[PDB]
Every structure is written in C-alpha cells, then in structure tokens.
Amino acid sequence: AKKLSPADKLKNISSMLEEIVEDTTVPRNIRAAADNAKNALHNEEQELIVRSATAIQYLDDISEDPNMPIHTRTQIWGIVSELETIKN
Amino acid sequence: FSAKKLSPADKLKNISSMLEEIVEDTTVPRNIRAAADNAKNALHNEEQELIVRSATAIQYLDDISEDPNMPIHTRTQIWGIVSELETIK
C-alpha cells in the first residue's frame, strides 16, 4: 500500500527534467532552464517545498520563450503540476 | 498578460492519452486498468462542468490508489495524471 515518497517524487521530476536537458532538438536556453530547475531540486540547503517553488519559477520564466516546441511545453506543464503537489 | 500555456482542450487530450496508456497496459491488474478507463470517461461527461468532471476522474484514481497490487510504474503515471487533473480550472 505504498504512497510515493518525497524522494521518489523528486527523482521522478528530475528524470523528467533531464529528458528535456538531453533532448538536443530543444533550444539551448530552454535546456539550460530545465537544468537550473533540476539543480534547484537538489539544493540541500533548502527543504523540499522551497526547492520546488524555486524550480517552478525557473520553469514559469522560460514558458515565456517564443521558440518552445509543443512537446516540451506539454512536458513542462506536467513537471510543474507535479511540483505543485509537493507539500510538507 | 496571461502566460503562454496549453489550451484546456490540449490539457484534456494529453490527460486522456496518459490514461489510455494505463488502459492498454497489460502488466496492470484489470481493476486498475478499468479505473483508468472510468476516469477517462468521467472527463467526457458533458453533463458536468470541468471542475466536477476532473474531480470525478481524480476520485476514480484516488480510490484505486489504495489497491495493494498496483505496480510502481503505474503509481507514478497516476501521480502525474492526478497532478495535471488538479490544474484543470
């Protein structure tokens, strides 16, 4: 009857982020934004909800970019929605 | 200004597609696959407004989440679908 642990959620989100970072079809700056978001989630000086908010902001900032591929936008939406579920 | 975002239509499409993935997934208990189809059809219940349909779909998935037989991969897929359903407003 396992629920998903905070560690598992962060690992899943980070993998979704690395999927964008490694999608060499994606513009450099968007890949950079996803890696910043990814690194934000591993800031050990912050608790999870503060890391999550930080990562959300890096992702919202880039969502404003004119050359984002349709597939990447759907991906970011999923990552952000998952980030917003993180509580405690 | 509102942010560049997916349309509600596109969110629903993407959620339905993710649900269909579990439905067609043979490694999943039939009851959990049926729950994911139930959730998917709940989204197209044009009898209700979007908030209620989303919640109904979430409810199907939350009810089946307490199933001890659920595979790890499916649990992650459902967390993603629920998260996205929760943004439907």
Image: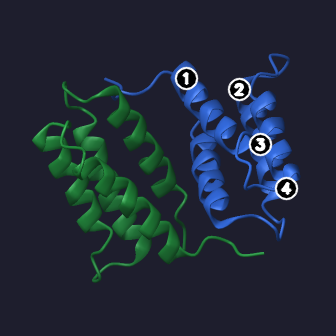
Chain colours: A green, B blue
A36 sits left or right of B66 in the view: left
Q: Quadrant of the N terminus of chain B?
A: top left
B37 sits left or right of A33 in the view: right
Asked if marks 2 and 4 touch (Cβ < 8 Å), the reply is: no
Q: Earlier in the sequence, mark 2 or mark 4?
A: 2
Is there any visible trace of residue B89 in the rendered image? no
Q: Chain of mark 1?
A: B
Q: Are marks 2 and 1 on the same chain?
A: yes
Q: Which residue is mark 4?
A: B63
Amino acid carrying mark 3 in the image: Ala
Asked if marks 2 and 1 touch (Cβ < 8 Å), the reply is: yes
Label 1 element class:
helix
Asked if marks 4 and 1 touch (Cβ < 8 Å), the reply is: no
Q: Nearer the viewer, mark 2 or mark 3?
A: 3
Residue B24 percent across, percent down from the top left: 72, 39
> In the orientation shown, which residue stands out farthest toward the left?
A28
Q: Chain of mark 4?
A: B
Residue A28 percent across, percent down from the top left: 11, 42
How far is the residue under mark 3 from the one under mark 4?
A: 11 Å
Q: Which residue is mark 1?
A: B8
Asked if marks 1 and 3 touch (Cβ < 8 Å), the reply is: no
Amino acid carrying mark 2 in the image: Leu
> In the orientation shown, which residue stands out farthest toward the top?
B46
> In the orientation shown, which residue stands out farthest toward the front?
B26
Q: In the image, which disc is placed on residue B50? A: 2
Asked if marks 3 and 4 touch (Cβ < 8 Å), the reply is: no
Amino acid carrying mark 4 in the image: Asp
